[PDB]
Image 1 (cartoon, helix red, strand yellow):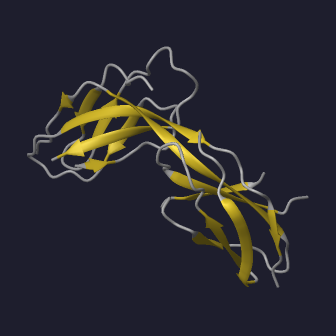
Image 2 (image 1 turned 60 degrees about the vertical axis):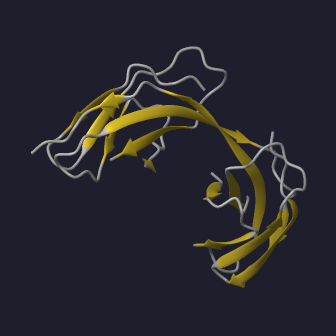
Length: 93
Length: 88
């Protein structure tokens, strides 16, 4: 059960890109795996996965000029499943 | 997430190795992806979870390879405050 990242703010570096700045929530139940950012116009919406969870900002590339956007974020905790049976298979010539 | 049962392996010739597995029964909710480990370690997960087989690339010939898999579930937390920003 991951809480949302607090204190969100975006600012456009160029007409075709906007960087997004966020902060860590204080007490979190367990570690998080990644962040998920989404872009919408929004009169379908695109999802962009931020790989490194230890990150406080990222730059959204590939946007349209002179267009307004709305952004949202969420923390993600992936639960690893049990390992399956081990199998062996060698590669030959 | 329960482990994917009945795992199987079968290589091509001298490059790629293909794996095959049966889905696990009785699982609480969906799963996000299947993670696969390859020791000559390196984890290489399959993006699409509704899958029964995948191709393992990058393998030197004449080498004893072994595989193991596991399921995963991305616990997507709550969304953050919505924010607006203009471009020009």
